[PDB]
Image 1 (tube, rainbow, N blue to C red):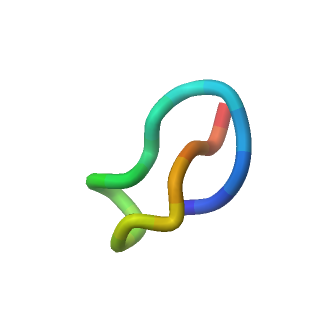
Image 2: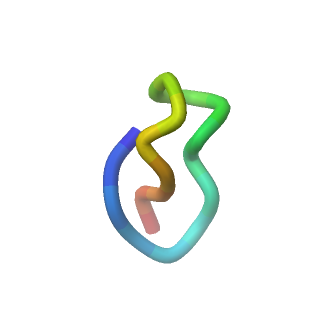
Length: 19
């Protein structure tokens, strides 16, 4: 749902990463 290392696109719309 934001920026970072580990993948987050499936939890937070598509925005990208969060690690």
